[PDB]
Length: 48
Length: 355
Length: 50
Image 1 (cartoon, rainbow over the protein chains, first blue to last red):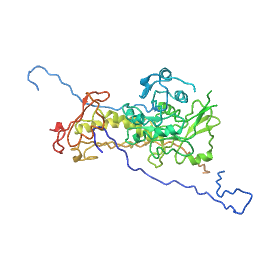
Image 2 (image 1 turned 30 degrees about the horizontal axis):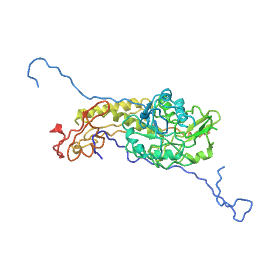
Image 3 (image 1 turned 90 degrees about the horizontal axis):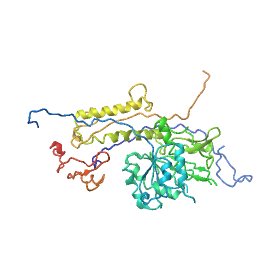
Image 4 (image 1 turned 30 degrees about the vertical axis):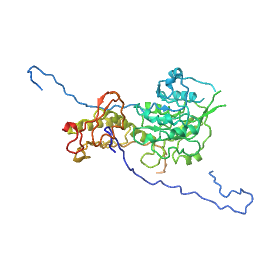
């Protein structure tokens, strides 16, 4: 809008875009439900 | 106009102008204090150093506002403001806050050194509306835990520094790092300028971080961009990462955001003396030149990422280009200007080969 | 000037007719502000073009 006199300023609307590469390797493994020497938690997350 | 023959004297008056730069520093703090005089209760006050703070205000005994403010001066100098308020939900002066910041023309950064969450999030929502009419603000924020705060959801001007920093005092007390991280922006613009991302700068005087972060959860927190205070063995504590909140390729970096924020505020302050002049052609070439001689000086000191050609600016103000006849009648001017900023260099990749 | 007007009270009185307030800035002071005549037609506005 252009209500009052003075100095207005606008900027750009849209910019460029590009794709980011990958991760390429995140596996999930096969636990066994009847197993005993383990935790009863179904989903575990291990990082290293 | 001339009747008696005599000799008449006359000069040529013109608003011919140029643009000069100010500093991008000196914020205000909106924590709670204890003033000494009743007129210092609810008005903005300029503080020059640590000496005159001890005259107007006091250091009490139980109380973290006096500790968090002296760490600002040990890192970087410069004056600062402060706005004392007592009650978090006192929406009287909180509504009366944003119409006091505009009358002082300088304010650039925004922060709050208060520890708890109920006081800070009441502040951050009070002046969140005053960020999107493009007057030139850039606030700072802290995170209560592993994810960003939601009082300002997605904006081009925030910055989050995750792990809070402690400090010894007679059990050491914790401190939200939004106070002392404002002072480290006052050193980078001194010698290096605005267009350098503050990362390798070293925090000046601290014991240790509160929680020790490692590289395997640095990988998770460096997207959804929030920054991090790191600890190293040889050089001690250091700030790390210079990414803003919203992650399109338009503005993902602190300096590219803060370079366009400072280049606008210097040319907008000097076009204000010429705001009612006629829209003829000799005014157009005088404005287009004073903008041309501002980006050229800023180009040849290493801040616009252009090569040895001229291609860093295309400021044009003509009538055939960039305008036409029918918006002259509803008096307008259009300044199409554009830069090509420089990006910080992270992720250096070597890729040795045999030949 | 006896009053301090606003930044936006100029805004709603800029169309239709031409209140043309007198507002004081920092630096330059007590200056006049706005040159508009009573009609809004694209031939006759802008007091200097009259």
